Image (cartoon, coloured by chain):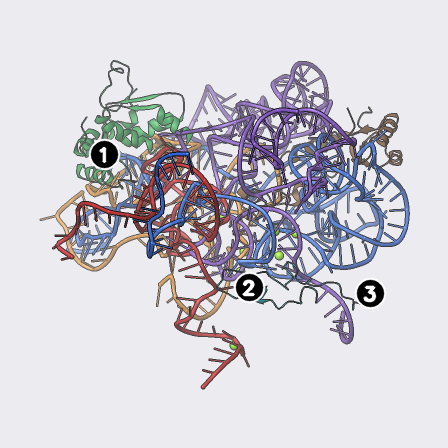
Chain colours: A brown, B green, C cyan, D red, E blue, F orange, G purple
Amino acid sequence: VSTLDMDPESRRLFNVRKVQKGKKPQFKRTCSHKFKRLDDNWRRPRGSQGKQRRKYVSKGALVQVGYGSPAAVKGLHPSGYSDVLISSIAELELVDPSYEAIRIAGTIGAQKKALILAKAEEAGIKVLNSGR
Amino acid sequence: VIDAKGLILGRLASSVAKQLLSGDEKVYIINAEQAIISGSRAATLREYRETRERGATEFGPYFPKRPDRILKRTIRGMLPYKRARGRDAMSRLKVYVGVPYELKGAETVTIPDADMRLLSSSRYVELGEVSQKMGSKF
Amino acid sequence: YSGMETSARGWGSGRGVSHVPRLVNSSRAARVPHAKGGRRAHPPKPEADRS
RNA sequence: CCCUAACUGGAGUCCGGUGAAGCUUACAUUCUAGUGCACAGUCUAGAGACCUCUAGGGGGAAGUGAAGACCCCGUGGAGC
RNA sequence: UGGGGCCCCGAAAAUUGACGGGGCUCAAGUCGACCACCGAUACCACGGAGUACCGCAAGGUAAUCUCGUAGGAAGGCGUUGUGUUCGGGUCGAAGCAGGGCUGUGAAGUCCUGUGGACCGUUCACAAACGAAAAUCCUGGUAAUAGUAGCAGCAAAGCAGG
RNA sequence: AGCUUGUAGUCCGUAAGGGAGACAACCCAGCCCGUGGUUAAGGUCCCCAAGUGUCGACUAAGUGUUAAUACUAAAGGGCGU
RNA sequence: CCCGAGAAGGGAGGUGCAAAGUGCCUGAAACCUGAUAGUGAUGGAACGAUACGGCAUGAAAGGAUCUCUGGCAUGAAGGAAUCAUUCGCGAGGAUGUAGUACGAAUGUCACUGCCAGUGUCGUAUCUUACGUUUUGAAGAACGGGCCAGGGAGUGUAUCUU
Ligand SMILES: [Mg+2]
Ligand SMILES: [Mg+2]
Ligand SMILES: [Mg+2]
Ligand SMILES: [Mg+2]
Ligand SMILES: [Mg+2]
Ligand SMILES: [Mg+2]
Ligand SMILES: [Mg+2]
Ligand SMILES: [Mg+2]
């Protein structure tokens, strides 16, 4: 375990993102709770008379770039590290453990996953998914 | 325990409704027949017989006849009584014709701003007169 | 003529059904790109020039 | 018909067996008024309303059935 | 006698109903003034996102940037395959049900279960490439409903074995 | 005529949010996200956040408690005040 | 082997890595049966969004100066209370106290074992579905019972850019 290298400005932006994404709406397509044929993913409302397209506050927030997280901490894991998806053993050499944590690919077999874990542990690299 | 004798009906009702919505007490109102309604007797009687005989029998308004029930209804219209807060407020209100035997001898209070001696004329009727002209026995 | 070798014709209005062409001796819809077994609208053409 | 009554058999009603179809975006115990594309169970303010079930005639759902056959329009037809 | 304020008469409609309702009379009405307060996403402050223009870059400027139908313009997500680069999989691929995390989002990734053999990825290139709607099509399946019908034209069965 | 046909401005159409009971187009306001504050229109008896506020009068008819308003009755009269 | 009228079926027991048990790979949804969580016979309807609570859950994939609760420092906009003087017919105003105490937040030090998330219900505010035709759609205008899958800018020639 190596301490996360995050300077105070990045810490402040990380806490800002925590607070702001705590308030971000789920951005479900309008009326997805009303029909089982509809998915929960976002679709832009298109009808002229649609209340969400007309931006009634009660109907839920529209997707818009104002909800973007701070650019310095955008995409980071909630632990503060950077998510790096490792699809094989050879990808662990490009990662430095100061600010990056590897996520092992979900289809990696147990035989190779054990070796990847041994190499990550010798390198000191944080692992987001393992067996514990 | 509020003594309704010589009190304006609407002003007493507004005071009691706000107190009930301040949510810390049970309010008892006694002598509801002795509450006052300002205005000429003909106009008040006309409006109360219009309200009394309005609705539909299967559906319509059932405006009460007893003065205590009329006073409770008057307070009922100044509350969100269809809401949990308003239902709680109405459950904590008891209105009486005269003094109930249990409350006999208890210390009462009167709302100074609902007093009928603040009226500038003699155009008023008591709630009991309205109730008995609507056919209520009390 | 894939999906198009039928003689299907529409029922018209007055039967409570869509106006799609149907088989002459059944209600099964035919020949239209949104009918099952119907023709592909805008398929690949052997006459297309890819060079 | 005044003015309906009683009675008979078959249904219905209740029980066993068998066993479909047609209306349906959702919700829905309503009533009044207003409002609103000027004909609202759902909006607004009131008034009511404990739930479930059975029977019953059809007030309402501008009930259901049918891309109005009346009128007009289409540089649409047909026959005469 | 003239000129003024407010009110009254003139003043009749159809389900029970409308100052929004309760109600209100030196007012909770009207008129002339005034005081304090409440009350938006407005305005101010801080933090954040994007955008426009400038800048070799670092970055700078925005009181004079941030709503939007028809519609134009830009950049991305996804599906299947091809060339090519680099991989994963019986120590468990795809798919499926549910969940965690990231992303404004299209979506991606991971976890658990199930499953038993295939699946991705770089840079590019293609297309039979994305559905909630068409009285859409095909299949499956509800409510209706244990309901209608199993009566009307020839009401037929019972006892015993 | 909530009729028909012009014109200028501004809106709805395509305009959120706040306020008028509700209100396409009436008032504040044009609106990236979050937090704090102060206001706008409008309101402050209760429903309902904030006045049972102040001063000076009027009204006795529950008149009224209705900015604009398609949502609000006239001529005429009154030794009512 | 047992039950069963049984050449049905069920139970038990086997085969097989796995029932995959014969229209048998995987085995979604609608629909139906049961269970669990929440709620529930005084209750108001676009079924949600937002905030705060009750109950349940919170293994993995989410947090560990993270969650809880406090102290201290700095703090933008904003900014008191109380009291003194004075003005006002009055409600109140002004001046001082005081740009002070406080204050979004930013740090720091302790304390704590939860928090995030998820399901359901409650309270508060807001919203009369969606697509379409429309000047105007919640409409008593048209379309859809539901779910799954299918379902619509393509090629040749030519001109222009
Ligand atoms: Mg013509
Ligand atoms: Mg557009
Ligand atoms: Mg579909
Ligand atoms: Mg205007
Ligand atoms: Mg239009
Ligand atoms: Mg406009
Ligand atoms: Mg608005
Ligand atoms: Mg499809």
Q: Which of the two residues, F10 or D65, is positioned nearer the viewer here?
A: D65
In this rendering, the label closer to the viewer, 3 or 2: 2
Q: In the rendered image, which residue does mark 2 sit on?
A: C19
Whether residue C20 appears in this view of the structure is yes
Q: Secondary structure at mark 2?
A: loop
B17 relative to A106 in the view: left or right: left
Q: Secondary structure at mark 1?
A: strand
Q: Which residue is mark 3?
A: C50
Crowd around label 2: few <14 · some 14–19 · many ≥20 (10 Å): few
User: On screen, F35 above or below E7?
Assistant: above
Q: Position of residue E54 (x, y in %)?
A: 78, 52
Q: Amino acid at mark 2?
A: His
Tell which subunit mark 2 falls on: C
**Which residue, given by chain and number where applicable, does mark 1 sit on?**
B38
Tag 1–tag 3 contact (CB < 8 Å): no
Amino acid type at image mark 1: Ser
Give the amino acid at mark 3: Arg
User: Across the whole image, how many numbered discs are drawn on residues?
Assistant: 3
Spatial separation of the CA atoms under disc 2 and disc 1: 73 Å
Mark 3 on the same chain as mark 2: yes
The circle drawn on residue C39 is none
Instruction: Name the chain letter of the residue that bears numbered label 3.
Output: C
| Labels 1, 3: front one | 3
x and y percent of residue C19 in the render?
55, 64
